[PDB]
Image 1 (cartoon, rainbow, N blue to C red):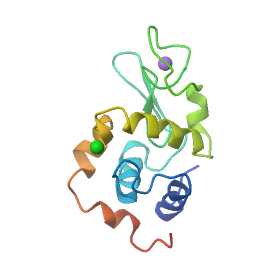
Image 2: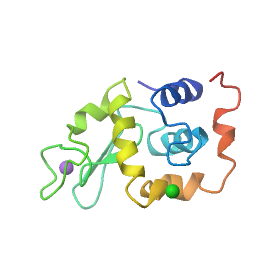
Image 3: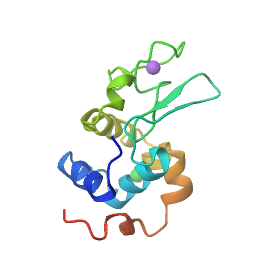
Image 4: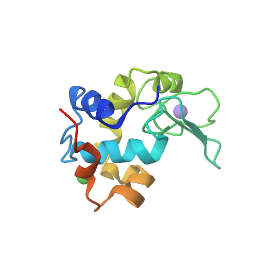
Amino acid sequence: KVFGRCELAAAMKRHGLDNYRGYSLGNWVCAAKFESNFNTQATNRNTDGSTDYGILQINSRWWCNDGRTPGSRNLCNIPCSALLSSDITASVNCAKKIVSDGNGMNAWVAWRNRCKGTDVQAWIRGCRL
Ligand SMILES: [Cl-]
Ligand code: NA
């Protein structure tokens, strides 16, 4: 599923992302935008053999099991394929563990490079939330 901007903002709000660990809704929508282009099906292979899955491009090295990342962890206790569903529940539940992990949303390179210290509230203007 390719989410519309505001459609994704509402889903994320419902699932408890709005100001989760101090990060406004703008921050999560901005990251989804640049990580996956709001596409739940997005995958991208990393040089280290790991793969990024889903709308928030969660990595197989740490977070999920794809059965092909030798020496990796499954800290969200999920198949990576769960992260590719049109329901974003598992992506969002797994993002809460990640953002809690000490580096905050710095864990997401695109957020750090493209969202951080920009006007992130733009990403949710015109949305009825
Ligand atoms: Cl933080
Ligand atoms: Na893994």
